Length: 50
Length: 298
Length: 45
Length: 50
Image (cartoon, rainbow over all chains, first blue to last red; front, top):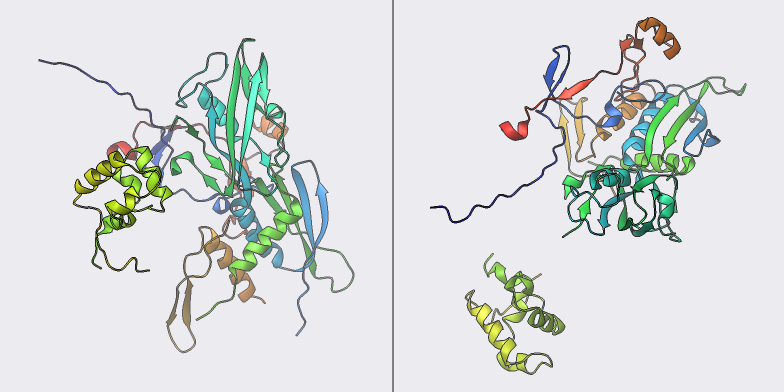
């Protein structure tokens, strides 16, 4: 019954955003709740933000 | 009533080509952290810099492609292009051409020398041509802007995440300033680690300019819409559209006002074209010689 | 090559000597920047 | 041994460092541990679920 089949492969790049889930190897897991600009981030004396 | 002691850029210690130590002299206490934070906040996000926004590589269509004769895939190449540090004279968009044939790394130094364009790090690797019959020819678009503007912030071309800000890292120290007079003065030492697009002093005067400008005081339907659509929305033949535009007919409202007589009297329009135009107009409930009486309002 | 500067103002007089002025549409991060600069000037200068 | 590496690292031995609040510039009132952690982005993404 099938005349023709078309498959379309679409590629998408996903950037980390609020609601995505991150975790470490020790069982510490959590969802991203806030993305705050670099200047608001806690930083070391030499200026490196975390 | 003791008027405040104001700062002025006093020293510049270029630890390197992209790392400096600016010092503002004689600042009243507590102002160290105040200006330190205001400035650190402007510098880390409000600085203007050039960044690659689009790239046109020959033979490549989608960024997912991989190239015959190139070590890294197109994605890696665009990711390399993100790190292209360019300082442009006085423009908000410049096209760089990169032609390279041979074996070995294709660095930013291989980019065609433009008079305006300054390439901060010529040894910056963009590619790696594997075989000696391999070659790349690409057009890198560099634009001026602010902050981090991703490619997702939207033709056989590709888009690259724009990192406009010239500054990577900022640090500051408050340190007591000298001079036996008054004694209770400090000096703000701003340690900068930029990408080499911007000079220390102008970065400071621009952060200060943005700050000061933020502080600028504190004070206290009828008619058919289709008529304002461009003629291109009618989807005429290229020729007809070009002829109409050549007659200063850029919108549907302009077209529906003209009559057959007037249109045929134009140098470039014949019976075929007029027939086509009447057909496309009739297909949308429109015609020639339409009165809209009031062309236009505001 | 600009920035969003001064737009729409509001004043909430909690009392005869207590008010709440609001400067609207300042680019993200400018809230704490102006907030701390001003808080520092007001609390000492 | 980790303390030793931290020494070549130049320390603090505890692994805590003075950290500045990016909003204020004032230091956080106590020393805070900061280190490189290895973190993974899990297959659960808001894009899929919402």
